[PDB]
Image 1 (tube, rainbow, N blue to C red):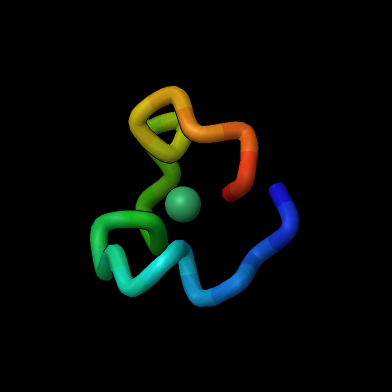
Image 2 (cartoon, rainbow, N blue to C red):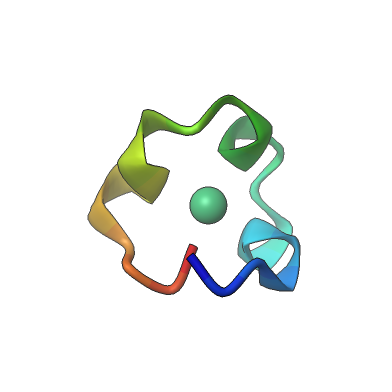
Length: 24
Ligand SMILES: [Zn+2]
């Protein structure tokens, strides 16, 4: 939820609830 380039995870651009990581 906080962005941070999804911690480097390209998949984050598609959501998927960040794999459960609130940090997204
Ligand atoms: Zn993410």
